[PDB]
Length: 25
Image 1 (spheres, rainbow, N blue to C red):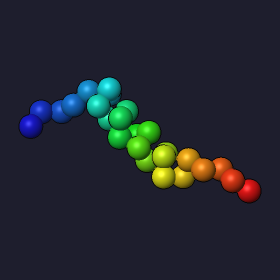
Image 2: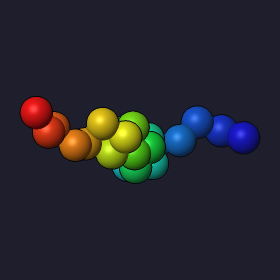
Image 3: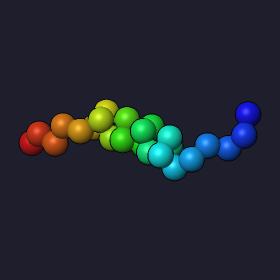
Image 4: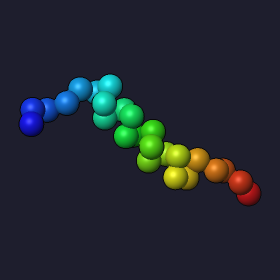
């Protein structure tokens, strides 16, 4: 279980943004 690369973490990063992707007002 060695460390991963940025390319992998990035996939998860955006996933977090999708939650509050909607910017309605």
